[PDB]
Length: 429
Ligand SMILES: CC(C)=CCC/C(C)=C/CN[C@@H](CCC(=O)O)C(=O)O
Ligand SMILES: [Mg+2]
Image 1 (spheres, helix red, strand yellow):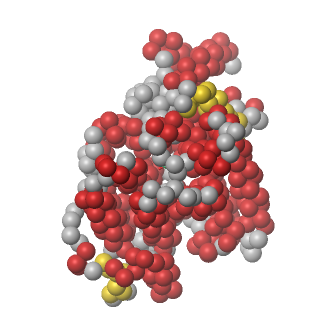
Image 2: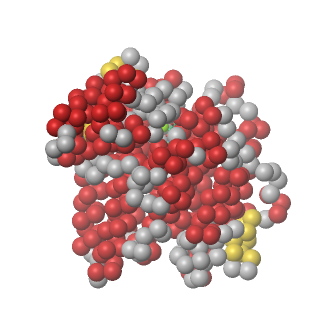
Image 3: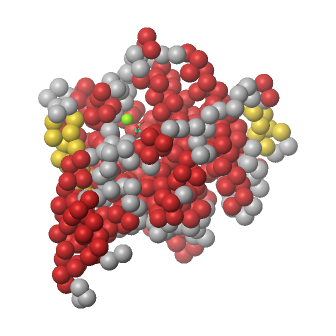
């Protein structure tokens, strides 16, 4: 469409997330207003316990939205039929928007597979969130189901894992840790014992859809060990979260929170699959200690940004595992607004640490092939960082985001109206 008809729609109906075209104009506005002006501080306007949360998320990477977002959104009802879900829950997760904005330069299928991975994290997260309830409301049967589900989910990823190198089979086998006694190595594959296939988990169609795509698209020609490795790390992290949330003794320091969030942010799973979509790819990077730290900085930045945006909702859940609340518990002078400022500052320092690791990783490359591979893999993680910022910025319609921001809806509608008018006025120049 033209800026004139979009301006007419915004002046009359405002901005929506139900019309997928609006997101293209929102992301275009954010790039022109911020990135294109050298301003890498994106506004986040929300509330927490009645306190105004008015902060800036720092991210110096180029904003973009996938050209496939229109088709992804147009097929969202078919996609949702895979899930055991209400549409109310599916709409708030909005994996179509997450994948399109964090993975903007991929094919339709390579963008959709990222949506599937992020949706898997959200649905498992909301299943684990049952442990947030008071002790008198916990149902042990739901916890038994959850513990069985993630073990069965893990085996489904094991079932597509047939590495060319036996060293990669040992890498995953040694990484199973407390899950290893449930598995056996059988004909070059890691298999769950038949005793523990006791149910069909509620999101098994989703997990099978993920495994089928990875098996059919990447397993024949690429080394998918890191995809499996990150899934193991995530599933073990969910188990750690169950153990952490199960014991109502919440004793996580900020560093222990970082180490825990390194496992459960799920973006490393999406990066592992996205890495396989590019010819520039170095499997050795995954065991490079500097690259592993770069992935951890990325997960922590997303976590800290998420902690600010989820603060008011998680405060009502009495959920203590949020960097905003951990800092307040350690410092009594902090209210919610001042704590969010500290989290935002920590996120800025992690971003600078990310950029410092990036320069060191690329300088350590031994040849052009490895440099271009590392640079491509780092670029993929940068896409997710700016994508997640814009994801939270553009929560402008209630029901189509985990954390609707009515102050962002008002701010973006006021600002995009002036920007679209400037496009119309100088047209066709
Ligand atoms: C690009 C994406 C999608 C990154 C993952 C975002 C993230 C860090 C999710 C963690 N989930 C939160 C609560 C989110 C919610 O409930 O909406 C938690 O459990 O700490
Ligand atoms: Mg949280």
